[PDB]
Every structure is written in C-alpha cells, then in structure tokens.
Length: 98
Length: 99
Image (tube, rainbow over all chains, first blue to last red):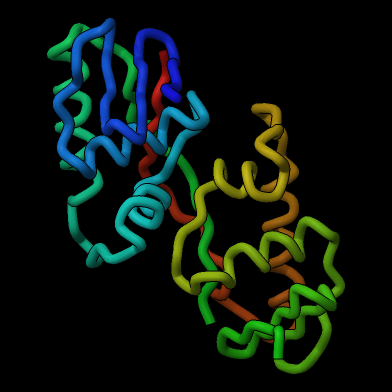
C-alpha cells in the first residue's frame, strides 16, 4: 500500500509520490532517495549513507551526485509548496582505516 | 573463516573477538559493535546518526556523550596496541525529511 507522512504520500510499487495530492514528478533516483528518507522521518541520512543505499557506494570520491539529486528533489518539493520538508544537516561521522 | 580482516585488525562477529596485531582487545559490547559496523566497509564514513540507529536502536538522546566516550576508548585501546590513525572522526553532510 501507500505510506503517508504529513502531506506526502509515497507508493513504491506505483512509483507514485504526491504532496498535498499533486504528483511529484521525480526522477527514478530522486524517487529512490525520497522513499528512503520517508521510512524514518527526521532521521538524518548522510551523503555516504544515501550513496550506499541508492547507488551501492558506486560514486567516485569528489562527486556531487548525492547533493545535486538532493537539490533537485528539494526544488520539486518547493514547486508543490512543500517548504521546509527536506533539510540539509551538517554532522559527524566515523571511519575505520587499516 | 567467519572473521573479517582489515589490515592488522581482525574481527569475528560470531565469537565477538577482535584482535589488533594479534592481541585481543578488551571492548565494551557497543565498542565491539562500533568496530563491527565500521569494518564492514573500510573507509566508509558512518555517521553518528547511523551508529545511533545501528547500535543504539535509534534512541540516543541529544546531548548524550556515550558515542564520544566509546570512540575515545576505542582510540586509546588501539593506541595501546600500536594502532594510530585507525579510527577517524570527520564532519559531513546529511539530509532529513520531515512532514
């Protein structure tokens, strides 16, 4: 079935997401990103988490792939009056080397 | 043969055993879990939020220092075994969706 969060309703099987009943015309990766973020609303997904979940980590160092898709996603949200829904949050991470 | 090896670090998820340069680390359960998460992909930066999600069930109150304290302990224990620069803390960017 569809999952609703605020005025967003997302149906992964139909590849259909609406904001206040109007279809968000997302690219496939934009849709995949939004379907990830809606699963735990307010959870901050880091760039590399989104890169891992949505691209299997197959993004080269120094690419802007995640950010450019996030920026396009937010624009599409704002176009349907979905202001303040997608946030960019600076944060902290940890990595193991060997 | 269930264990993971990254450089001089070997982590066995079944035995919950970690050695560095052959010597067993004495770790708290969540310190072991941190290493078992981070070793899954050497160099992958795991955010504090996903460490919270993966290891604290997503229920770390804002202002808790427990991740910080465990990271400091991990660094100290690696340094004790001649392990420097293994655990990196780096700032980054994330995205969150609210309704």
